[PDB]
Length: 367
Ligand SMILES: Cc1cc2nc3c(=O)[nH]c(=O)nc-3n(C[C@H](O)[C@H](O)[C@H](O)COP(=O)(O)O)c2cc1C
Ligand SMILES: O=C(O)c1cc(=O)[nH]c(=O)[nH]1
Image 1 (tube, rainbow, N blue to C red):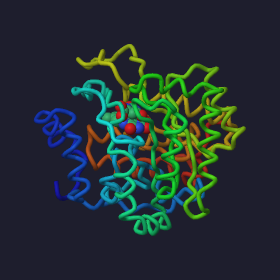
Image 2: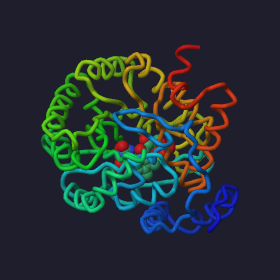
Image 3: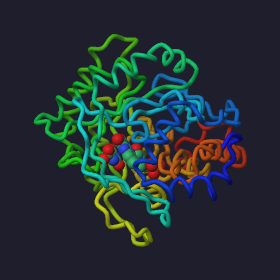
Image 4: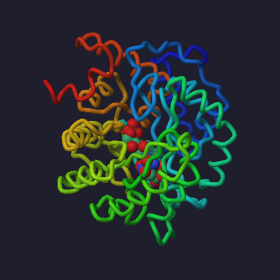
């Protein structure tokens, strides 16, 4: 627990955290432990090969902690200490709200998957604002060091006007963020995903873009859309088209999935909610691929979904991701996995004659 070995956390400690605590308390302990920085300071040095400049920022390694782990920005600094190259803080809603009734998270250890239906449990804009404000200049220094911060916006359950909620996020948190995320891909909030529709998405993102533009230069973040893995091809076409039109700065590719692949062994496979972890991977990768192609490599993509190795990582990059985020992999292999991905990602780049992550982005669309 002090040295930071993968093979220990994998077989012993992590199956015991699981064996002892329900998935929610485990997450909360993890957030506590991480904000306190109890974790090992990662053995692995980041080589220059992993550096990516994208979105008006240098990223020291391309492996991000995904939205959901740190819903309320309590653990940003420990996440960096864990070795992520960039941190994203979990969907924040304008007003605080509590989320769906427990139980709302489940492990499918046999599938290395998770299903969650939290439905945007948030401390809300005020609280997260003060939290981020209180390290604002630390963050400024971090970004310049190649550790950018992303903020991921969602909408209140009751909210009558979707576009106005996100507007509030841009206004309140936009100034504290290197990039902002319009999350319209959560499975768990009645009607949210239908904001992925062309007309409804253009009107929403016009307003987001507009607000963003009204922020001062130094506090003017990049704006991306996080989309679902369950989109029809018409949907993807459209998202793609609107994106190019309004000049959106990027996409985060794939929230969790409401599909349930043939093969899930998990006793809890038929729980309502978003499916994450391994069963999402290739689905997720394929969506990076369609989106990269549709936007013609001119729209940066953050790949997320089932990443738990260098290969997993490098696959999405070759697919066209500029950056990847993982989350679930953390509930199975623990902190070490960040080290792993980075180091396996590194090896593979060399093995396949790449100079660095930058050369390998979209690599598949040129081979
Ligand atoms: C417990 C849980 C909560 C999540 N919460 C959010 C969320 O608030 N906002 C969001 O954009 N994504 C959320 N995600 C989805 C992740 O951001 C990610 O898109 C998905 O899990 C695929 O990556 P992974 O398999 O490595 O976890 C959540 C995922 C899980 C595991
Ligand atoms: O908080 C949630 O319920 C949630 C939001 C989201 O965007 N994705 C997810 O899997 N869960």
